[PDB]
Image 1 (cartoon, chains in turn blue, green):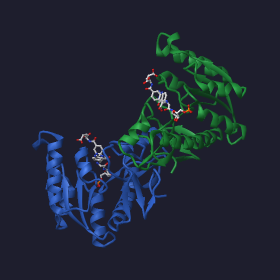
Image 2: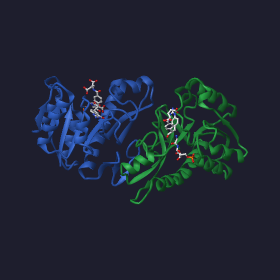
Image 3: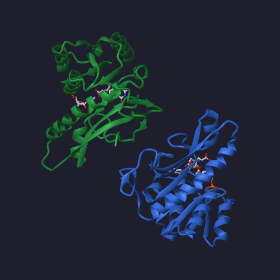
Image 4: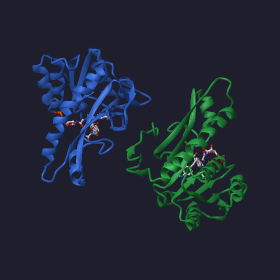
Length: 209
Length: 209
Ligand SMILES: Nc1nc2ccc(C[C@H](C(=O)O)c3ccc(C(=O)N[C@@H](CCC(=O)O)C(=O)O)cc3)cc2c(=O)[nH]1
Ligand SMILES: Nc1nc2ccc(C[C@H](C(=O)O)c3ccc(C(=O)N[C@@H](CCC(=O)O)C(=O)O)cc3)cc2c(=O)[nH]1
Ligand SMILES: NCC(=O)N[C@@H]1O[C@H](COP(=O)([O-])[O-])[C@@H](O)[C@H]1O
Ligand SMILES: NCC(=O)N[C@@H]1O[C@H](COP(=O)([O-])[O-])[C@@H](O)[C@H]1O
């Protein structure tokens, strides 16, 4: 089972995934890590793990379509069974989403449908929500509109800073992402009729309950 | 629980609603029926049931805003708890949608998002669909774009005419519309964050599953 991970920054989720393959919780391997930022430390994590790395700079391309095309061309050298977005700060084109339909995953730092887009933690905190979390879902063209597979809620108390809750959510992300990937790896997770299904059963709008 | 129904034609769905109140499946009453067509037989259905009727001709108004305004003014004489569109062939203005936000329902003759608008049936046959149906949803300015509450699928077999399938879908409409209205009447159905919620639970893009 071949996994290709796409990142943009630190890659703590990438690390959790790497560790899960190592323990075999996930019966597969991370074949490659792609980044749109040369600096991403995640690349360094993959490097140290003997995993291949690649970098595609948006400037070197003259259109989003041209960029994803070279992305698809590159990612495919590894014959991935699933493409995983772990902190990938770049919106993917419909062509790309199409090419990996049903095998493209992402983990959004909020309790979807709440706060699609960037700056989740802040909104959650500035709006005064008593509950925050993360959501792993199948990627569709709709910015975080795809079928939610699993969420991990997290209590928000007075006094918690943006970083406090962020580190709290992160801890959950490291737990549910590798898990969702393992479900996928065992052919227990699929998507059709634009819905997420676990063990053959349809999952609710907010993921496995 | 006061219900005000809006129609344009025969009103078979109106009748199903009327019958449901009679049996108390819906714990409420149709207080009035409005139509934008003087001929609509639905008016006679209401008439025979001792229900009040009203007609608002578009020609008698010089703008859509003026028309809905008078419509709101009239509908409100009946202090409705919910306004139900049953075959109402007229697009309502934002102000109107706003005035009945969360308490405005419609039943579209197709499996939304598929075939928003008119000519559902014909497109289904034509586009050679193996499945057709109806969708009850909360009305938002987006033509059949609002939160779908419940759909009723219907199989399509070679040998089926546009009338064969239409009559098949109607039969379902008479079943799920009164049902959805009862959910609403029991305070079990609500809309917020532009989503449909049944028994406190968020409903999928396709309605109750
Ligand atoms: N089609 C599709 N592509 C996707 C590509 C990435 C992510 C991950 C993530 C999410 O899950 O949170 C996410 C990341 C970046 C932006 C964004 O708007 N970034 C730029 C704008 C344009 C771009 O460079 O792509 C920015 O610099 O602001 C939004 C969401 C999600 C999706 C998705 O759900 N659907
Ligand atoms: N704001 C709003 N109003 C609504 C009013 C009615 C219906 C129901 C229905 C649907 O669900 O089927 C529907 C009704 C009218 C047309 C329509 O195009 N009518 C005219 C155009 C403008 C007019 O009314 O003069 C036409 O003659 O083509 C299409 C579909 C849905 C909505 C809706 O979703 N949002
Ligand atoms: N563009 C996707 C996105 O929303 N990513 C989010 O950014 C953080 C980076 O974690 P990381 O250590 O896994 O890089 C994670 O919390 C992840 O959910
Ligand atoms: N513009 C709304 C719309 O498309 N309505 C549809 O028209 C038919 C009229 O039924 P009826 O008059 O016998 O209830 C119904 O099938 C309804 O879903």
